[PDB]
Length: 60
Length: 65
Image (cartoon, rainbow over all chains, first blue to last red; front, side, top):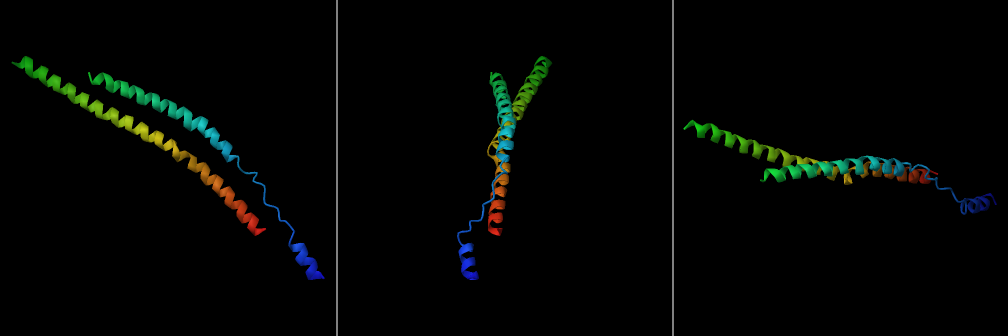
C-alpha cells in the first residue's frame, strides 16, 4: 500500500501559503503622503491663492 | 503734442506688461494645478506596482510549491 499510503498522504497534506511579511510599502506610502500629499499640496494651494489674489488687484 | 505720445506709449506699454503678467500668472495657476493633479492619483501607482508585485510573487511561490 505504498500508492494508497501516498495518495492519502498527498491529499490532505496542506501546503503552507507564504506569509506576506512584505507590505512595508503600505508604510513607505503613508510616509510619502506626510511628504508629497499634504506638504506640497498645502503650499501649492497657498501659491495658487496669492496668484489669484494677484490677478484680483490687476482687474482694477 | 509730445506730452501725449510719451504718456500714451507709456500707458500702452503698461497694459502690455499687464496683459503679459496676467497670461504668465494664469499659466502658473495652471501649472500648479497640473502639479497637484499629478501628485494626486499619480503617486499611489508607485506603491500599487509594489503591492501588486508582492501579490504575484506569493502566488507564483504558492503554485511552485
